[PDB]
Image (cartoon, rainbow over all chains, first blue to last red; front, side):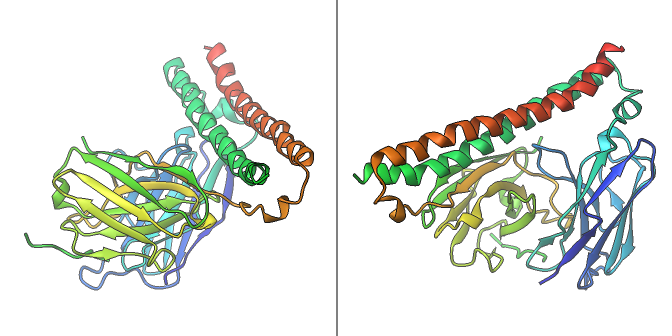
Length: 165
Length: 8
Length: 171
């Protein structure tokens, strides 16, 4: 079974900083037939599915700016953001897409430095800013519903015992 | 009519 | 436009079963294999099942072999996941995704996700000898706890809105 190790687990970044992410595979991801690396990088914003970012280790997907570079081969892979932007704040996952079972790294999380939001957002228009303000509500709502569901589980045994009387 | 296995 | 819509999530007790659905549109469904991929609460991504475009090949990791069955109705544009012998560990957001039978590039198309919760701490045999009064106290106590956790989520997002609001106010 192929193990993917992503390092570091988390990264606190200021705007414009260069960002380097590591994905190490226990076995080679070099495909027998075409000799490409079947290594795929995803970017995940909260409340959203992972979104495909780079495939075959180094081919950018549609819409992905050249800020991003995937590199490396066989077992040691790197995702590089030359100049991090607010829209880049996310969790980055690498995936073995070469042999079953398909497996994923644990993810490298990018987070803005506390107090730094103004510099990240200084070029954002009010339209852009409202959109980012409205996107927060589904994430909050999804997190609250995990609570409701957690406490429904905690209630059932007590309810089951009470009804057993 | 002619299935294809997965590539992994 | 490629779209995928999961459904069927629910909260269930261990050992129960459940069947998930995925509606597909915007592409020729019978030309693509499909996969199910889940995200557990620690936010790890775990591949769970794959099926070939025609349905005759199925693949599973060892963790769900014998319990999960993936299937498809190609005339209905629907992908399925039957989940049996559910463990607490199976709690996750389950995602439907297209297998890139031609690009062989990974997962480009995902659904929105449907939440499966398999309950932990469900056995109550030790609670039966409690008095009904004490069970009520224990039952009622979960309310201030649950309200307090919800209130912290609100505090957290108040904190996240504030820099965006400050930048909006600056114009």
